[PDB]
């Protein structure tokens, strides 16, 4: 028993992290087979930050302008290309530590682990979720660009995020590993602001099911709700709408606990109305929304 | 910016995890140099576990009664012995992935990363504090015994915890890597309870400093206090005593933020006596006590472990 925000073990990703230097800029790269992936903004100068023309900046570069260091070893760059907002540096060594892997673009509400890195060396691992407004609430300092987010299925690493920038509210924006940003953001220093963020309803419900599995029932009630009445209430608290997809997704946890999905929705409605009245749920005094239904089943079994 | 509960990168420890089977029991072992460490209770049947005589149970065992698999390779056990509550299985092959390491025993209030494992295979990593009542609020299912806890310092892994059991309240008990339990627990299937827990005061203060570093300042106030006055408040609220060493340890953060420790103590006094009044700190409505002063400095400075 117990319930913790738990990340995937990071070793398979650690063995892929390298340092990429261009000019006076150093950040992190992800080395898989013979390619190093990193944010294309590594080629920006201090003049290039508002309206960089990346095509024009890249055509001016030679392979030897990119310094790639893996541990204490310099890799040889033998080719380069840009794919959306990521740079792909072809190197003359396949990484012998390359795991089984895939690139996956995720949807808001999905969770993943982040291996924060600086100078090609991993610092820490934590769990994050893609917010409804396509940001993540990360922990990243200068130099962390190119750190990645991932899940592990069996022994297969699914890379879903590459870190590019911090927005003015202190939240973080980035791309998938094909270089497409999550959300409406661009790799320019022009003013950009995240949308107002909302709570990931389906994840809160998942986490309430986790609480019941771990033996806590105090927040349940004798009521139920229609799906539409639930959404009408929950949106008044800045909760994302709950769709029938989400209701279906919660089927397994509902079956395991014996609490119907819309019955749990009624519990959530009451919690939003009442607060916790000095109680806690799984050690929290707030409703937690960065555990998915899949996470809950994986951790509680 | 941002502040997250953060574990050490777990790769160096992943390369050490193996599967240990004895009879019908499978759990995890730690393979370092040519020795595999795991809980001595692996040798018990359920009858045994009621009142085990471990020396007696072990005499019966041959090396070949211990099936150790590293990945999909079997390890040959060539000797076996106990140290306190850990079994040490001498194997015929040194682990080629052994990291630089030490065995250290931590103190209550100190944090560490747990690599949760099942059948020798790492499944998850998370950060824990050794509670004042010597339990940890972990997340472990059947099969997790032998999972370990650790810190990293430079390139050296300091192993500090091996998981042994779950208590009736759902918190967790285990040993250091020399097999000495944290807390007043025994490796026997009985009646045991965690003592009443308290809050780790120095860590709450550390986390308040983290909040300030991250722009969350509403709880700051113009007041300061004394150790003795604050410690009376702490005792009243089931908070650990704050000592002068704690104050010294927080010195760096006091210098960096402009908030003396006793100035922050007055913030904490007011939070305890009045609550948060609908507000949050670093996204929490509870006062978080599982970040040490060192953790806050490390995360708000970007220290790495290549
Ligand atoms: O087996 C153990 C070791 C730790 C501990 O407290 N137990 C335990 C727990 C419950 Cl709930 C019931 C019983 Cl008989 C024993
Ligand atoms: Cl997804
Ligand atoms: Cl909370
Ligand atoms: Na003050």
Image (cartoon, coloured by chain):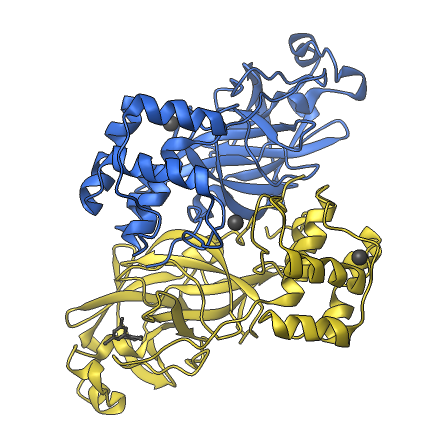
Chain colours: A blue, B yellow
> In the picture shown, does residue A250 fall above or below A83?
below
- Which of the 4 image quarters holds residue A294? top left
Instruction: Residue at 56% x, 25% y: name it.
Output: A174
Which quadrant is home to the N terminus of chain B? top right
| Viewer-nearest residue: A40 or B181 | B181
| Viewer-nearest residue: B170 or B93 | B170
Residue B148 visible? The answer is: yes
Looking at the image, residue B223 sits to the left or right of residue B66; the answer is: right
* Residue A110 location (% of width, % of height): 41, 32
* Residue B248 location (% of width, % of height): 78, 69
* Residue A273 location (% of width, % of height): 44, 38
* Residue B40 location (% of width, % of height): 30, 79
Instruction: Residue at 62% x, 54% y: name it.
Output: B275
Instruction: Residue at 73% x, 41% y: name it.
Output: B215
Instruction: Residue at 28% x, 30% y: name it.
Output: A225
Residue B62 visible? The answer is: no
């Amino acid at each position: 028993s117990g319930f913790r925000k738990m990340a995937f073990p990071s070793g398979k990703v650690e063995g892929c992290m390298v340092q990429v230097t261009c000019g006076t800029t150093t950040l992190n790269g992800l080395w898989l087979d013979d390619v190093v992936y990193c944010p294309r903004h590594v080629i920006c100068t201090s003049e290039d930050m508002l309206n960089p023309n990346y095509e024009d900046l890249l055509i001016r570069k030679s392979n030897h302008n990119f310094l790639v260091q893996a541990g204490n070893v310099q890799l040889r760059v033998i080719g380069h290309s840009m794919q959306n907002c990521v740079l792909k540096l072809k190197v003359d060594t396949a990484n012998p530590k390359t795991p089984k892997y895939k690139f996956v673009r995720i949807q808001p509400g999905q969770t993943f682990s982040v291996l924060a890195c600086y100078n090609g060396s991993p610092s820490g691992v934590y769990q994050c979720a893609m917010r409804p407004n396509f940001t993540i609430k990360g922990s990243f300092l200068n130099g962390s660009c190119g750190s990645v987010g991932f899940n592990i299925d069996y022994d297969c690493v699914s890379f879903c995020y590459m870190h590019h920038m911090e927005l003015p509210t202190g939240v973080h924006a980035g791309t998938d590993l094909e270089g497409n940003f999550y959300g409406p953001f661009v790799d320019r220093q022009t003013a950009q602001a995240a949308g107002t963020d909302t709570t990931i309803t389906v994840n809160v419900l998942a986490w309430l099911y986790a609480a019941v599995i771990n033996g806590d029932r105090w927040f349940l009630n004798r009521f139920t709700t229609t799906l539409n009445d639930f959404n009408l209430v929950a949106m008044k608290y800045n909760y994302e709408p709950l769709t029938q997809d989400h209701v279906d997704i919660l089927g397994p946890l509902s079956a395991q606990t014996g609490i119907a999905v819309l019955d749990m929705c009624a519990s959530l409605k009451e919690l939003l109305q009442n607060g916790m009245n000095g109680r806690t749920i799984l050690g929290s005094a707030l409703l937690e929304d960065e555990f998915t239904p899949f996470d809950v089943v994986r951790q509680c079994s």
